[PDB]
Image (tube, rainbow, N blue to C red):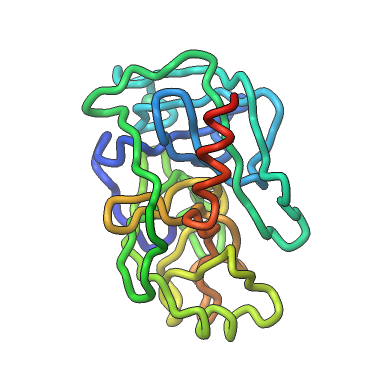
Length: 223
Ligand SMILES: [Ca+2]
């Protein structure tokens, strides 16, 4: 997250870190057994880390739970990032508590102009590299479909939305991929892609989770 703030320990209790020997992507806990992330974050060998603040220090509220199964969307296209969504099942249910909590899935799609909370342990620099240890947060508005398409001509599908600031300076970034975009208390987006981070006229692009609620529900009913 570039241009964000330190969230505060465990104030985003649905945020997970996906670990394969190192943090590599975020995700969101949607119930005691299941995480939603980006399909482009697929790796074999995922451990889900819940209750994290500093990902490099064991502080006492963590739950580390291996994935048993990962399910990339059936129509994920890794070239365009259309349908950039994945489900990860935990080998055992998380113990839900004040610091490890699920986020609701949406009923309706979010509205342009809504300010959402985006969070992660990704790079904090637009030019260069610096990865934080503690979780960072950003409030960013959903942009109109016409603005998003103007920013990325011939690249935005109905399963994507843009959020952020066209003047640059505030965005998600590498290592935030897969993490949450929460709008009116529901998971509306997944950190998916963008050209660079926090560059002028190149806002973040996010998987539009409201398009996937029936897939998510039937998949969790069946696995
Ligand atoms: Ca930790």
